[PDB]
Amino acid sequence: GXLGRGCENHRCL
Amino acid sequence: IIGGEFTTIENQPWFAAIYRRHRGGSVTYVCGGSLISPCWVISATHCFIDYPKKEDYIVYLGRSRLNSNTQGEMKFEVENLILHKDYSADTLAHHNDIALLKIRSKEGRCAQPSRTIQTIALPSMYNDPQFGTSCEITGFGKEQSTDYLYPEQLKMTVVKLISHRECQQPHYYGSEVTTKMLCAADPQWKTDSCQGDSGGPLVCSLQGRMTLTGIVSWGRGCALKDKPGVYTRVSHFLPWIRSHT
């Protein structure tokens, strides 16, 4: 799902 | 980052390494940033939006390695964390993806310029390099898809700026990319920024002056054919930067 640039330090990562 | 070269902080002296302390006391790398004045680091809002508590962050300047010390490195706390109020995220795209960190040492001091710590110039209003210009990106992000740890040594690479017209082609990003963003990639799709490089600098030589043209923001995969890196267009946000500093 939520992967890559834009998704650092996210609960969804 | 993918491809490029290992570098050292003396070659990228505006580069800020941003970490977060976790409950339990473990520290992990979050994102890169750029020193734009002695007290101010610029980065991406997406790096902080899920954990916006400024006390948890540590900012290093003068640091070339992720988990060892570099002589001359300075450690900072975040005095003020300013995220863009109109930040939003879609499936791929991130909008108004820009953040400001006012930094302070435990003594209350800002950055002291040195061989390994320098500021980077901001661009002028609505002044960007022409598309096709070669620009530099720097960070501690993934080197390949299968990486489960970030590299120990700082990296850099060179990519070329891509026109908005090209980037909005249907096999690129369509209308998901906007004119407040800048695309950049390798013509052979062999090098790119990747996860962990967000927040860090896209630097271009404008008028012989090294200038912060972009901030690593988003992209589909890393070094994927027809999927450029997407960067926040710093020149659009000068009024926001000026009003918040």
Image (spheres, grey):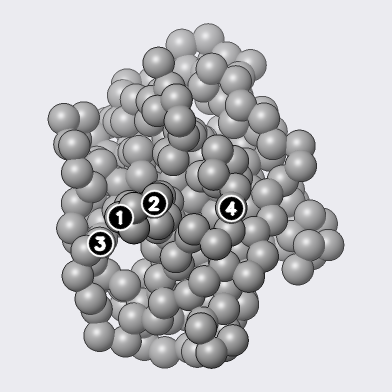
The residue tagged 4 is: B53
Q: Secondary structure at mark 2?
A: loop
Q: Give the residue pinned by disc 1.
A: B26
Regarding residue B62, the answer to whether it shows in the image is yes
Residue B22 circle label: 2
- Residue highlighted by disc 3: B66
CA gap, disc 3 and disc 4: 22 Å
Residue shown at 60%/48% (left/top)? B52
Quadrant of the image occupied by residue B26 = bottom left
Residue type beneath disc 2: His
Under mark 4, the amino acid is: Lys
Which residue appears at 69% of the width and 36% of the height? B87
Between B146 and B76, the residue placed more toward the observer is B76
Residue type (three-letter) at the residue carrying disc 1: Ser
- Residue at 45% from the left image edge and 25% from the top image edge: A12
Q: Earlier in the sequence, mark 1 or mark 3?
A: 1
